[PDB]
Image (tube, rainbow, N blue to C red):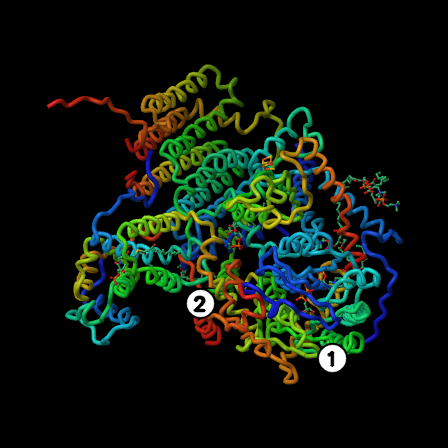
Amino acid sequence: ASTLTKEDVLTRSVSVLRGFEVKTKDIDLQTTFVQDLGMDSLDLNDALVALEEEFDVVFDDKTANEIKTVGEVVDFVLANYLPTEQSINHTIR
Amino acid sequence: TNPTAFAQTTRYVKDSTEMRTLVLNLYRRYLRHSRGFVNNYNLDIPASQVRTKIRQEFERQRFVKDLPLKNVLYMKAQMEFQELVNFWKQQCHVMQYFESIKGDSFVQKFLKGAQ
Amino acid sequence: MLQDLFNNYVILVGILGLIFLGVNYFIVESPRMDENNGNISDYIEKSGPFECGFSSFNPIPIAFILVALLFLPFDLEVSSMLPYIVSIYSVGIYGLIIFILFLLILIVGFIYEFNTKSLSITTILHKKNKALVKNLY
Amino acid sequence: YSSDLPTDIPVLSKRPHTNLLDYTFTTFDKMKNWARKSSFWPMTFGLACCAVEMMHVSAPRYDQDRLGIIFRASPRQSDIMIVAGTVTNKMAPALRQVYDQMPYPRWVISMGSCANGGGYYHYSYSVVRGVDRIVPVDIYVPGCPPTSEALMYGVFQLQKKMMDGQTHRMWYRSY
Amino acid sequence: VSTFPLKSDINITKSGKTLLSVGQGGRSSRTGFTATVFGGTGFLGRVVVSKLAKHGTNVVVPFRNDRARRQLKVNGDLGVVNFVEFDIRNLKSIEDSVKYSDIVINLIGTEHFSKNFSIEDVNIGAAERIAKAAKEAGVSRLIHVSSYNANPSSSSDFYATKGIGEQVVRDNFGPDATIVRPAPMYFRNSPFLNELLQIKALGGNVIFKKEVYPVHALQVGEAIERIAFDDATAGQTYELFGKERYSKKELREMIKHIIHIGYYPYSAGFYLPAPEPFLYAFALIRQYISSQPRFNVDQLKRSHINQEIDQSAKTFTDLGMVPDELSEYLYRYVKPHIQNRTVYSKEDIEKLRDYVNTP
Amino acid sequence: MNLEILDLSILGFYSLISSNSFESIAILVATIMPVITELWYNYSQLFALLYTLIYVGAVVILFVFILSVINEKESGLFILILVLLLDDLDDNESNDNDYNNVYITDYADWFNNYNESDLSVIGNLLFTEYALLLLIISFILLMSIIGLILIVKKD
Amino acid sequence: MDLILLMLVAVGLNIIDIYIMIEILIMGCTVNTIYSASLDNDMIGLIYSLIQIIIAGVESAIGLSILVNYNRIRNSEEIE
Ligand SMILES: CCCCCCCCCCCCCCCCCC(=O)OC[C@H](COP(=O)(O)OCCN)OC(=O)CCCCCCCCCCCCCCCCC
Ligand SMILES: CCCCCCCCCCCCCCCCCC(=O)OC[C@H](COP(=O)(O)OCCN)OC(=O)CCCCCCCCCCCCCCCCC
Ligand SMILES: NC(=O)C1=CN([C@@H]2O[C@H](COP(=O)(O)OP(=O)(O)OC[C@H]3O[C@@H](n4cnc5c(N)ncnc54)[C@H](OP(=O)(O)O)[C@@H]3O)[C@@H](O)[C@H]2O)C=CC1
Ligand SMILES: CCCCCCCCCCCC(=O)OC[C@H](COP(=O)(O)OCC[N+](C)(C)C)OC(=O)CCCCCCCCCCC
Ligand code: SF4
C-alpha cells in the first residue's frame, strides 16, 4: 500500500531543501520555488530530481514548465506513490 | 528496421522557445541516471560527484545564441546521452572523461621552452 | 556377490579426485614467477567475466519449460516398467495384457500433447505480414 | 652485520649445472616447458587481412594441428594471443581487456605490419601506431601479410624461447 | 607529469654532461638522461620506471626474472626502456647497467632471507656494491630507498640492516648520494595491503596492532621523479609519510566493512587467536619447508614497533608536493575485492572509521 | 567409527546457514546421497539405485532447471554450534531399549530353488496381484500430463 | 529438541525451499518403508515404496508447474 501521507512528504521535503542553497530556511506548503528560494533552471532541477531520489516518484515533461510551488510537489507524491513489486520470495512465504 | 533504445528523430527545430524546453528535460534525464552511471561504469566518484560534473558540463555552455547552432548542439548532446545510457562507451573513456584537468609567468615559460 | 573389489575401486576414484584438485596447487609456478603483477583475487581484470572483450550489464520460453516439466511424467512411466523386465516370463500373458494397458493409458497423454502442439517453441511474437489494399475515395 | 657477496658467479642464463639439484630443477623446467612448447594454443584474434594467413596455417598444406596448435576462442583456454591485423583506437581498450584475462604464463605475437608499428595506416587518425603501445609483445612477424611460413617461423622462434625458460631453477639459484 | 617534467630544457649533471631535452613531453619526446632503476621489476619499480620512460628518459632495468621484465617496455618508446640480465653476485653485470647511466636509483630491499641471500646481503651487500660501482663509472646522481624506520642499533633485522645500508652507501658513493625513506605505500597489489585483505591471517590481532603513516605510492613514485631531475637534492635524507595516522587493525576492520564480510568472520578464519610461541614456531617451521616467501620471524617483532617520524629528515613539502591521505584513495584500491554500489567518498571514510571504533 | 554420522552433522549445519536458493538445492542432493549410500549398504541395493534413477535423474535436475528461471538475488556461530550439540544428544528415534540393543539372526532355507531378484517378485505381484494399483498410477500420470500443460501453456 | 520445532529454522526462505522440505519429508516415509519391508522380508512393502517414489514424483512436477506459471505471472507483461 501507499504509506505516505501529506505530512510525511512535507517533513522529509525540508531536509532535502535544507541540503541546497535556499534564500530562506523557512519552507512550507505556501513557499514557492523560483521566487522564495531564488532558483533558476539548473538550480531548481537538482532539487526536483533530488525529491525524485527520496520520494521515488518520477516527474514527467508536462509538469516540468508547470511547477511553481513546493506544496504542489508534496501533494503530487501522494497521487503518484506505489510500492515496488516484491518478488515471489518476499510476498508469500 | 527497429530503432534502438533512447532514439530521437533528427529534426531541424524552427522555434526559439521549444528548444529551451527540450534542453531542460534533457538535463533532468542526465541527473535521473546519476546512480546508474556510477554503477554501470564503476566510476570511482560517487553519485553527487557525477551530478556536480554534469552540472559543470551544462553550466559551461548555456550562453550560445545561434538557433541553427542550437540544434546541432542539441543533436550531438543527444548522441552523448544515447551512447552513455545504452552503455556503449568503454569503462576507460568515462573514467578519463572526468579525469581531464593556473598558468605560469613568462620567466617560467621562457626557461623550459614555452610552446 | 562379494563387492569388496568394487568398494576399493570406489575408494580409489574418490582418492583420485583429490589428486586432480591438489596437483595444480603444487605444480603451477607461483605468481611472482611469471609476472608477479598480482594474485588471482587481486587480479580483478583476469578474475572477471568474459564478454568478447567489451563489458556488459534465462527467461526461457514456455515450450522449453514445458518440455522439462513433461519429462517428469514420461520418465516415471519408463522407470516403472522395470518390474516387468525382470519378470516378463512368470507373469505370462496376464502381465503382457496389463502392460499394454499401462501404456495405452499413457499413449493418450502422448496423443494429447501431440495435438495441442505444446512442445513446439512457437513463433508468435514476430513474422506477421499483411496485404496492401487501395482505399479509393 | 656480516656480508660477503662474490663477484665471479655468473647470471642465470649462463650458469651451468653444478650439483644434482641443478639437474633436478632443470628437469622440471624442461618437462614443464615442453608441455607448453607443444600444447601451443593461440587465440583467434584475427582482425584484418593478416587473419587470412593465420587461417592458412590451419589449412591442410601446413596443418598447425600437427605441431600441437589448437586455436581456443576463449582467453582463459588460450595461452597465446596472435594479434593479427590493424588495431584501431576503437579496439585498443577492448584488446587490453582480452589480454589481461589470459592466465599466466601468457605470450603475445604481433603478426604483420599493422600490429608491429602501424603499417600502411601509420598516419591515420584512428589507428594505433603499433600494438606494443597496449600489450607487451614477445615476437614480431614482418610482412604484409606475412606468408603462412613466416608466421610458422615466428611461432618456432617463440617456441625456442619457451624451451629456454628456467623458472624452477631460478628459484633455486636466483631467488 | 602534467605536460613536461623537466624544470629547464638544458640540465648539466655533476659530471659535466650537458643534456638537452627535446619535444613537448610526449611519448616520442626525450630528456637526454639515462636512469638505471635497479629492482625495477618490483612493486615500487614499476611506478618509478613508468614515470621515467613516458617522459623520455632512457631506463636501464637490471632484472633477474625474465618473464617479469616484458611488461616494462610498454611504457617507453623504441629504445627508451633497456634490459640487462644481472645478479648481485655478478659484479660485471652490475657495471653494464651503470656505464651509460646519469641517474642511478636503488630499490632493492627484502624482508625475508632466502636460501641464497640474507637480509643484510641485500639491504647492504647489494646496496654497497651497487653504490660503489656506480661512482667508479662517473654516475652524476644516486638515489636510494630504505625503510621508514631505519636504525643502526635496532633489534629488528630489517631496520638494522636498512640503517647500515644508509651508512655503507655514503662510505661508498660519497656525499652525492641521497636517501629516501618511504612510509608503507598503498596501491594495486601493494604488499602493505595484501596482508590486510587475506582472509586466513593467523595472528591477526598481533600483526595488525602496529601503527603506520600510509602514503600514496603514486606520490612516492613522483617523489623520486622530482628528485631525479634535480641536482639540488644531493646528500639529503627524506622521509615520506601521510598526514592522517592509521593503524592496521583500524584498517583491517575498515577494509572488511566495505566488503561487508554475521557468522562468517567467526568461521572462515578472520580472527585467529593463536599463542605467541605458536606464531614464532610456525614462522620458523615454514622458513625451512616453504618455497614462497611467507610471514617471517622479523615481522613478528616489527608488529610490536610503531612507525617513528625522524625530524632530521625532510617531508613532501620540501619538494613542493602535498602528500595525499589514505582516506581519498583507500576505497578504490580495494574496489576489486568488494543492487547499487556504495562509493565510500573521502569524507565518508571517517564515518566508516567511526563505525569501527564504536564498541 | 560410523562415518555416516559426520556427513549428516555437516548437512545439519549448512541447512541452518542456507541463504539463497543455491544452498537449498544442494541440501536436497546432500540429503539424497546419504540416503542412497546407506541403502546401497545395509538394507536394499535395488532401491538405492531406484532412488538415483528417479530422484536425481528426474526431479533434481528439474529442480535446477526451474530454479534458473526463478531469481538470483543477494545469531552467529556459537548458537548454531550450540543448537547442533544439543540436537545431537539423543538420536534414538525409537524407545524400545530391548529391541535396539539386542541383535538377532535368521536361518536360511533351501526350499526356494527358484532364486529370483527382488524386482522380479515385485513385477510378479505389481503386474498380476495388484494390477489395479498399476493401472491407477498410469491414470494419475495421465492426469499430470494433461495437468501440467493446462497450467503452464498460456494459450 | 524437536518439540521446539527446530526444523523450521533449517528451511529456506523461498517457496522453492518449502517444496524441497516436503520432498525430504516424503522421502523419510519411503526409507522407513524400505526399512520395514526388508527386515520383514516382505515384498508387499517394497511395492508400497515403489508407489511412494512414483507418486511423490508426480507431486513434484505439479508443484513446479504451478510455481513456474505463478512466477511467469509477475513477469507476464509482454509489451514488446
Ligand atoms: C564432490 C563433493 C564436492 C563438495 C563441494 C562443496 C563442499 C562444501 C560442503 C557442502 C556439502 C555439505 C552438505 C550441505 C550441502 C551444501 C549446502 C551448502 O551450503 O554448501 C555450501 C558451499 C560452500 O560454501 P560456504 O562458504 O561454506 O557457505 C556459504 C556460501 N555463501 O557452497 C555451495 O553452495 C556449494 C556450491 C557447489 C554445489 C554443488 C552441488 C552440491 C554438492 C553435491 C555433491 C556433494 C554431495 C554431498 C556431500 C556431503 C554429504 C554430507
Ligand atoms: C536430555 C533430555 C532431552 C529431551 C528432549 C526434549 C526436551 C524437553 C522438551 C520439552 C518437553 C515437553 C514435552 C514433554 C514430553 C511430552 C509430554 C509427555 O510425553 O509426557 C511427559 C510429561 C510427564 O508425563 P508422565 O506423567 O510422567 O507420564 C507417565 C505415564 N505413566 O508430560 C508433561 O507433563 C510435560 C508438561 C506438558 C504440559 C505443559 C505444556 C503444554 C502446554 C503448552 C504447549 C505448547 C503449545 C502447543 C499447542 C498445541 C497446538 C494445538
Ligand atoms: N609499500 C611497500 O611496498 C614498502 C616499501 N618499503 C621498502 O621500499 C623498497 C622498495 O621495494 P618494493 O618494490 O616496495 O617491494 P619488493 O620486495 O617487491 O621490491 C624488491 C625489488 O628488489 C629485487 N630484489 C630483492 N632481493 C633481490 C636480490 N637478492 N637480488 C636481486 N634483486 C632483489 C627484487 O627483484 P625481483 O622482484 O625481480 O625478484 C625487486 O625488483 C623496499 O626496500 C621496501 O622494503 C618499506 C615498507 C613497505
Ligand atoms: C611423469 C611425468 C609425465 C611424463 C614426463 C615426460 C614428459 C615429456 C618430457 C619432455 C622432455 C624434453 O622436452 O626434452 C627434450 C629437450 C629439447 O632440447 P632443448 O630444449 O633444445 O635442449 C637440449 C639441448 N641443450 C641442452 C644442449 C640446450 O631437452 C633435451 O633434449 C633433454 C636431453 C635429452 C634427455 C635424454 C635422457 C633422459 C631420458 C629420460 C626418459 C627415460
Ligand atoms: S599488415 Fe598488411 S596484411 Fe596485415 S592487416 Fe595490415 S594491411 Fe592487412
Q: Residue at x 55, y 44 (%)?
A: D123
* Mark positioned earlier in the residue sequence (1 or 2): 1
Provide the secondary structure element on which disc 2 rests: loop
Q: Residue at x 72, y 63 (%)?
A: E36
Residue C128 drawn at (x, y percent): 29, 27
Question: As shown in the figure, which amino acid type bears the numbered disc 2?
Answer: Ser
Query: Are the numbered discs 1 and 2 placed on the same chain, yes or no?
Result: yes
The residue that mark 2 highlights is: E345
Kindly give the residue lying farthest to the left in the view shown. C137
In screen coordinates, is C73 left or right of C50? left
The residue that mark 1 highlights is: E155
Residue E93 drawn at (x, y percent): 81, 60
In screen coordinates, is E240 left or right of G74? right
If the image is split into quadrants, where does the N terminus of chain E sit?
bottom right
Closer-to-camera residue (E299/B36): B36
- Residue C106 visible in the shown view: yes
Residue C35 location, quadrant: bottom right
Chain of the residue that carries numbered disc 1 in the rendered image: E
Closer-to-camera residue (E34/D44): E34
Closer-to-camera residue (C34/D99): D99
Chain of the residue that carries numbered disc 2 in the rendered image: E
Question: As shown in the figure, which amino acid type bears the numbered disc 1?
Answer: Ser
Provide the secondary structure element on which disc 1 rests: loop
In this rendering, is residue F116 above or below D109?
above
Label 1 environment density (alpha carbons within 10 Å; few <14, some 14–19, many ≥20)? few
Closer-to-camera residue (E257/E132): E132
Residue D119 drawn at (x, y percent): 60, 41
Residue D52 location, quadrant: top right
Residue B27 drawn at (x, y percent): 30, 57
In screen coordinates, is C110 left or right of F4? left
